[PDB]
Image (cartoon, coloured by chain):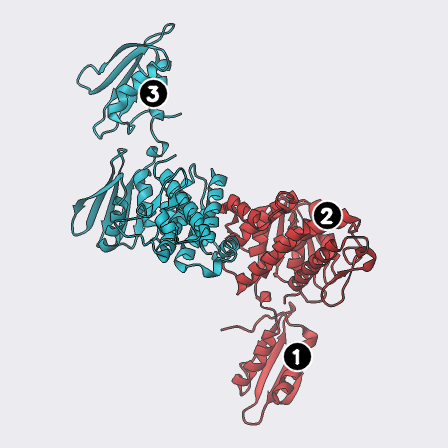
Chain colours: A cyan, B red
Amino acid sequence: IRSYKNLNLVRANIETESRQFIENKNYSIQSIGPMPGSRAGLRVVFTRPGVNLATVDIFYNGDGSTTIQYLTGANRSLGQELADHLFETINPAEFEQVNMVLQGFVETSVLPVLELSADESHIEFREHSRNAHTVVWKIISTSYQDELTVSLHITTGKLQIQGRPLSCYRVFTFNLAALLDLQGLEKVLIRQEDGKANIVQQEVARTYLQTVMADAYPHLHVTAEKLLVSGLCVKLAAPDLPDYCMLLYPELATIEGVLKSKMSGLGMPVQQPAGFGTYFDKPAAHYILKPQFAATLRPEQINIISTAYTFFNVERHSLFHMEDMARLMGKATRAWGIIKDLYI
Amino acid sequence: IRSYKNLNLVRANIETESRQFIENKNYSIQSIGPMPGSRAGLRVVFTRPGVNLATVDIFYNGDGSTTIQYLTGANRSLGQELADHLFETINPAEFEQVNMVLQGFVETSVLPVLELSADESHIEFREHSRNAHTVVWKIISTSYQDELTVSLHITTGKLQIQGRPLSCYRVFTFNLAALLDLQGLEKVLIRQEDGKANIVQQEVARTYLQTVMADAYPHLHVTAEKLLVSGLCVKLAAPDLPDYCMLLYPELATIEGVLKSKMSGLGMPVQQPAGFGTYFDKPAAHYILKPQFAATLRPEQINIISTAYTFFNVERHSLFHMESDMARLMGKATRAWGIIKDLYI
């Protein structure tokens, strides 16, 4: 049916997006102006040779949202075109809100996660409120207009996450995945409460994972294998969803927890402020090693590590900014191939 | 913390099984004889130098069971030894009863399965009762003393299985598995009602099977892949059990539905009465082809088909006669996957 009320629309674009739409359809502007009367908003009257006058109202509601009113005037079928265009200027995920509770966190365990998330560019976090019972932080996307509210009840150790599954949610849970248990990781990856990844036979999934990495399996770091097995359980137990692009977190994060492990193992430690950019270059669409440090290594390891970091950064970026199931599983198989190749 | 009442003990062995215990312990027999009165059974009084007289009574109940009474006489610490020996001569599975209902069956869909089941040695099936609503058959293991009650309500098409998960149950469900959908197969493999195989991502299990079967995946018998993926979902969704040796049925049946397909596909059709024995000999627990038919094929096929039939029959035989719990099953399944892959050129 699709509803047009209470939309999180970019306010400053509302007018321009319309003129660039009507000229896009070779219509004619009658009048574009602020709504008459004590209501705030925008009345757009426009039409085209052959039909009637389309009138569209746009109320700016009190909470920052934007309600479209296309059922008015003399031509509604023509206002619904503008309504559908503007409605489709919004990322679909914005129609979902998340409000979930993870268990077992303190200030000294959460503060580094917000710190690491804010080490990203389009991410800032500030302390919002605090009392004896609760400390609440706000994460803001400078690029978009998305905010994410993290409320830590210290008196019980409960971390409450509220907001929208946009860039902020994805960056924060990516930095969070290294700490979560099985049920917490499930809860953040599928955004549903009663997942069933716990009832997965860890032995059969372990046989799977051992099957994928042939000779590299007995040399696997346990901090990588536990997370990959958990993530595989998550992949297996997920119910129907529209977008599974988020279920790659187990592998991606693991790659980090392994790349950091081999990078520093060959004279390239990832310092906390330095990060990864201080070690790699981007030629085209395939990041390579800085030649100063690539010269000391065999070309095999060079190509392996280059493909690894390129994959990591490309997929992380395309998951942070929102570029169904077979595609995800193939990407996961590629990630597993990379992880196996890292081990000689 | 076990109880000794209502045991399905092999009656004619009850006494013999006992003496080879008492002589085994260099104990001494006081008296072994039938109990007084209208009860049938056996009273065993024995002891050894150093202790008191142990008395063990054994009543033969009316339903075929056997109640042991070791809390009698002057010595219980010694009577419980004999009682525990007799109690441990029984396969543990006899202590479970199954009573389940499968959906979607008619008379003509069950009869060929009972015929295929009765093609076995220690398995018989007979029509027990019949009315307008329900026809009930009894499967009997002549070897053991296990019976299985199969009750088909035609008015709704519901097949009820009652009894014990012993040899009869295992043979019947193996000949039945090729027909079942996913949830019926789960119901027979875990013997529980609220299994969770339906909520398994069939796509991830499909990726798993595609990983294991390299080139044989685009060459797969489709009726084999449906059953294999179903069984993989069941394997992944199964709750904790004592014996997982039974969750291997998906691969085994597949091999049959493939061997029969390639056997006949290479000039060796498996007739219904003839079976598979018409093509192989058994030297040393590793079935080989009769040279008569191995000579007509390239040396490649000989070892593959021989190892395939050898593995199938070994595992089926050890499952019909009850020889980590889950790692064991997964390793057996990995070998089965290697075999199924090698069967496809």
Q: Which residue is mark 1?
A: B17
* Same chain check for tags 2 and 1: yes
For badge 1, the amino acid type reads Glu
Mark 2 or 1 closer to N-term? 1
Task: Residue at 68% x, 67% y: name it.
Answer: B144
Who is closer to the viewer here, B153 or A330?
A330
For badge 3, the amino acid type reads Ala
Label 2 to label 3: alpha-carbon separation: 61 Å
Residue A83 higher or lower than B319, as above or below: above
Q: Find numbered disc 3 in the image and state the secondary structure of the residue it sits on.
A: helix
Report x, y in % for residue B13. Answer: 68, 76
State the mark number for residue A83. Answer: 3
Contact flag, marks 2 and 3 (Cβ < 8 Å): no
- On what subunit does the disc labeled 2 rest? B
Task: Residue at 28% x, 44% y: name it.
Answer: A161
Who is closer to the viewer here, A283 or A61?
A283
Q: Which residue is mark 2?
A: B261
Q: Is residue B242 visible?
A: no
Q: Find numbered disc 1 in the image and state the secondary structure of the residue it sits on.
A: helix
